[PDB]
Image (cartoon, rainbow, N blue to C red):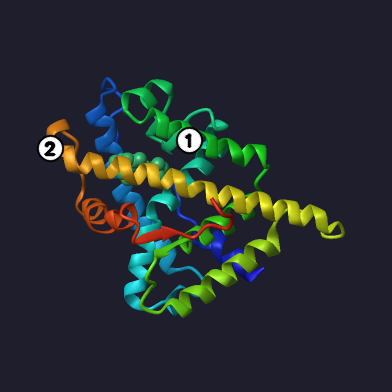
Amino acid sequence: PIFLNVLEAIEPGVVCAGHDNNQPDSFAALLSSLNELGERQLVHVVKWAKALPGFRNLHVDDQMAVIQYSWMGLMVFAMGWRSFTNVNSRMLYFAPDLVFNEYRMHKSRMYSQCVRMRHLSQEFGWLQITPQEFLCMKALLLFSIIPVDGLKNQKFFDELRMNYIKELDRIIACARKNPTSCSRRFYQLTKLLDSVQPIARELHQFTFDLLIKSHMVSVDFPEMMAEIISVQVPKILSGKVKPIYFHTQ
Ligand SMILES: CC[C@H]1[C@@H](O)CC(=O)N1c1ccc(C#N)c(C(F)(F)F)c1
C-alpha cells in the first residue's frame, strides 16, 4: 500500500483564512478573505505537489506550471470534500473560519458559482466516495490541465498521468468478482473528475474579472495570487492551456 501511504502522509492539514466573523458580511471583506485563503492554500498545494510520487520526473519549469494551472481545480475539489465531511455539503467550508451559508453565497456575488461547487460537494455523498478514492482523484487532478502546444518535456508528464490513472483504478470501491461493478465505478469517478473542470473555469473567469476591477471594489489580492491570475490564468481563458477530459464534452 505504498502509494496510498504516501498520499495520506502528505495530505495538507487545516488552513484558516483569517476572516473576521464578528463583522457584518460584505462583498469586499468576503472576497479579500477568499483571496488570502487562496494564497495560503497555494503555498500548501505547492508543498503537497512536490512531495507526490514521481513529481520530480517532470522538467523543472513544467513543475511550477502544472501546479499553477491546476491550483484552482485542486482547491475546489478539496473544498468540496471538506464541505462534505464537515457540514454534509449544506454549506461551503472554505476554511474553519470561512464557511459560506446561503447569505454569504449571495453577498459574495458568487451565488451561481457556489451552486456549482455545492453540487460537486453533494456528489461525494451521492456516490459514497471513499477517503482513498478522494486522495487518488485529487492527485490525478494535478495532471489534468496542460498547454495545447505541450510542456517542456511532455513525455514525462504523460507517463505520470498514466500511472496516476492506474493507481486510481487500483483502489476504486467495487466488487472485483463482478467486472460490471468496477466498470460502473470507474465511469462514475471519471465523470466526477471531468465535472471539476467547468467549475474551475467559472472560478478562473470570476477571479480574473475581479482582479481587473479590484481597485474599484476595494478587494485585496496577495502577491503570488495576483501573478498566477494575470500570467497563467489568461492562458487557460484564452484556450492556450486546456483541461484533459476523460469523456468528450
Ligand atoms: C482564488 C480566488 C478566490 C476569489 O477571488 C474567487 C474564488 O473563488 N477564490 C477562492 C479562494 C479560495 C478557495 C479555497 N479553498 C476557493 C475554492 F475553494 F473555491 F477553490 C476559491
Q: Quadrant of ligand 1?
A: top left
Instruction: Tell me where residue 82 appears, x and y as whole percent.
Output: 51, 41
Crowding at dot 1, Cα within 10 Å, few <14 / some 14-19 / many 20+, comes out as some
The residue at label 1 has a CB less than 8 Å from ligand 1: no
Instruction: Tell me where residue 178 appears, x and y as whole percent.
Output: 86, 56
Q: Is there any visible trace of residue 37 in the rendered image? A: no
Residue named by callout 2: 215
Residue named by callout 1: 116
Q: Nearer the viewer, residue 37 or 245?
A: 245
Mark 2 / mark 1, whichever is N-terminal: 1
From the viewer's perspective, is 106 left or right of 176? left
Q: Nearer the viewer, residue 62 or 94?
A: 62
Cα–Cα gap, marks 2 and 1: 27 Å
Instruction: Tell me where residue 95 appears, x and y as whole percent.
Output: 40, 39
- At 34% across and 66% down in the image, what residue appears? 65
**Amino acid type at image mark 1:** Arg
